[PDB]
Image (cartoon, rainbow, N blue to C red; front, side):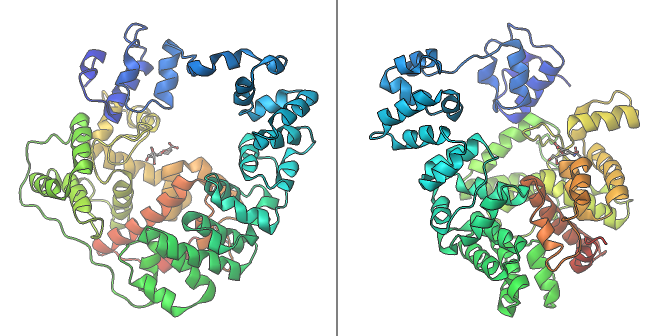
Length: 516
Ligand SMILES: CC(=O)N[C@H]1[C@H]([C@H](O)[C@H](O)CO)OC(C(=O)O)=C[C@@H]1O
């Protein structure tokens, strides 16, 4: 089914409407005329849909009309500009780097009283190492502007300077990136001297991972303990408490972790080590067959999803009842997950006839992936237009459907059919598992591609033998999305294996991750 640009224009703005506009663009069916009003019809104007629309109608915009005149000067004529224009242009470090040194000296004097930040950057670029100049001034705003301009600067930072960094908004991404990318070794080593009193949440956690890579186990414990105390989500606290346990072996930490209300790999592992029973999994069995809702209409899903997320505690109960049918089971579970404030564990198995003939280990992996990818919503669409319950990128979906399986009249929208999603997921999971084996590694490759996974596993510092392995390696997976995805999918997998009476010990999974 196709939609003309005219029909789409009548739908509400959503990712579904964006997806269908993008299908028109990629088929060259949007004329320069149709493209005129089109911006106000796009829900999320980022990435491919933007670069495609801008092939038809470029934008030069935007320069704020107040400062238009400021952008008529160059490095050769900036001394002719008024003081306001001079200071606007000096917001750009590339602009500052382009100036000649006599003009940087002149402008540094001009701005020393009113804008000593500008002065510091001007004089820093008069040296062969601007980062060293800025660090000597302990100019923290300047430091982050220089880092954003170029990641290549690296220098030792003293105790006073590093303890000032965590107060700046840029600190969190700075610390994450240099620790997981294993860049900027002098910055990295310097961050051993950050007082745990000065950091919290994710930043404290990454500084703990940092301390472990230098085998500073007491500092690491202090960082992870501050993370456990400050993190807002129970899942993240549990990850931090697990590290506290692994490092200092306090049995109260493991007891606290085994009694967590969050189901995650860390609380599951702690339950297993202490002979605690498996957590209770909800049982959803609606007797009603169906209602009026079309589970194959992507526009209906965008609409009802927005109602569910904005619904007060009251309106959730009305929706819960409406969607308490077998045909709408994924929507029911989605509503209940909100309605019970994310306290109960739901692990549904919808459209199960399509998988009941696979072995149970394969069933569990399919279901683990689908739960994480879509929550079993058949018409799910990601911001990069991954499609259906198993969130297939269109390129891969077309390769499998057209080239490999030669399906008659295949269209990428077949990914919205549960039978197609499960079938293709099985097919792709076979390719990955045959090469990768561990369900964790499969999960990383499913989310991030087999290329990145192969490169990570080729490194001699990832998933090898060690004191704190394989846990440390799971913290150092270089893409945040994939690092998180793997932990979540692995927990789902354990749960579904258990529900299918095909249990495995998560300790066996961890042992199989270490190659020799
Ligand atoms: C089965 C499949 O398509 N896997 C792909 C995955 C997926 O679409 C994502 O996990 C959606 O949530 O995305 C990507 C990607 O780098 O974009 C590559 C994977 O090969």
